[PDB]
Amino acid sequence: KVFGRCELAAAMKRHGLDNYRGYSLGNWVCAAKFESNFNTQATNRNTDGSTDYGILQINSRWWCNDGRTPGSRNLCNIPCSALLSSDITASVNCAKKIVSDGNGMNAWVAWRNRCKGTDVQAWIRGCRL
Ligand SMILES: [Cl-]
Ligand SMILES: [Cl-]
Image (cartoon, rainbow, N blue to C red; front, side):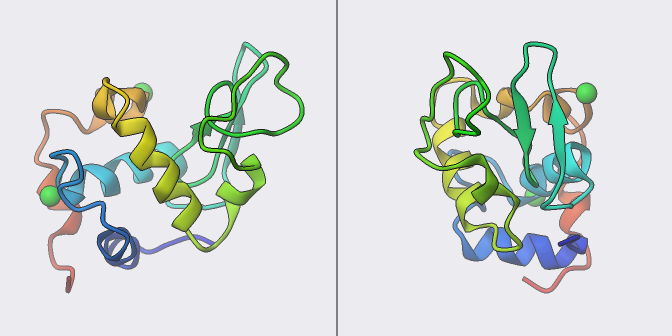
């Protein structure tokens, strides 16, 4: 599923991401835009052979099991395919664990490089929340 911007903002707010660990909702929408273009089915392979999955491009090296990342962990205790569902619950719950692990949203390279230090509130402007 390809979310609209405000549709995704509302879904993320309902799932508790607004100000989660101090990150306002626009940060999460911005990160999703540049990680996946709001597409829950996005996948991208990394050089080390891991794969990033879903709307927030969660990496199989640490966070989910895809059966093909030898020596990886599955810290969210989910198959990576669960992160491609049109229901973002699995992605959000796993993202909460990632952002809580000490590096905040710097875990998402696109957030660091394209959202951090910008007017991220612009990403939820005009939405009914
Ligand atoms: Cl915001
Ligand atoms: Cl980037």
